[PDB]
Image: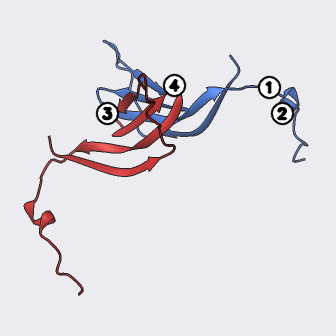
Chain colours: A red, B blue
Amino acid sequence: LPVVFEDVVLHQATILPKTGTVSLEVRLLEASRAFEVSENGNLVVSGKVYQWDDPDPRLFDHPESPT
Amino acid sequence: LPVVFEDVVLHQATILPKTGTVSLEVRLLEASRAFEVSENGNLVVSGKVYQWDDPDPRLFDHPESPT
């Protein structure tokens, strides 16, 4: 699955406790191509995600360096 | 439930057929206070809905008339 993220915003940082677990929920809106990652009812990450219909290997050719 | 809708968008109009039925699907994103109505995977409405915390009945007082 090639993927294309777009307009990702990290609203807050999650600290991993030395003991225990942190549970993250991920919710998608396929019609709007949008996703929200939440933590205990607080927004953590938001943006758009969708499958890349036509991958082009040219996109990963290294640009000529300015220096 | 006193509600509040913000930034509502109607993307396409759904035609109720003479026979049969149309299925509409509502997906809520509590963290982002957003919703989405979809029909067969096509976005029909988008926006924000959330509970009105403290209704202020003054808001419904009739505004000073234009004439």
Q: Kindly identify which residue carries mark 2.
A: B59
Mark 1 → mark 4, Cα distance in angstroms: 26 Å
Frontmost of labels 1 and 4 is 4
The N terminus of chain B: image quadrant: top right
Q: Secondary structure at mark 3?
A: loop
Residue B25 position, x and y percent, is: 39, 21
Residue A23 position, x and y percent, is: 41, 24
Q: Specify the label residue B55 is tagged with.
A: 1
Mark 3 → mark 1, Cα distance in angstroms: 34 Å
Q: Are marks 3 and 1 in contact (CB under 8 Å)?
A: no
Tell me the amino acid under the disc marked 4.
Answer: Asn
Tell me the amino acid under the disc marked 2.
Answer: Leu
Question: Mark 3 or 4 closer to N-term?
Answer: 3
Frontmost of labels 4 and 2 is 4
Vertical placement of residue B25 versus A32, above or below: above
Residue A7 located left or right of residue B40: right
Mark 3 → mark 4, Cα distance in angstroms: 23 Å
Category of crowding for the residue at label 2, using alpha-carbon neighbours closer than 10 angstroms: few (below 14), some (14–19), many (at least 20):
few
Mark 2 → mark 1, Cα distance in angstroms: 8 Å
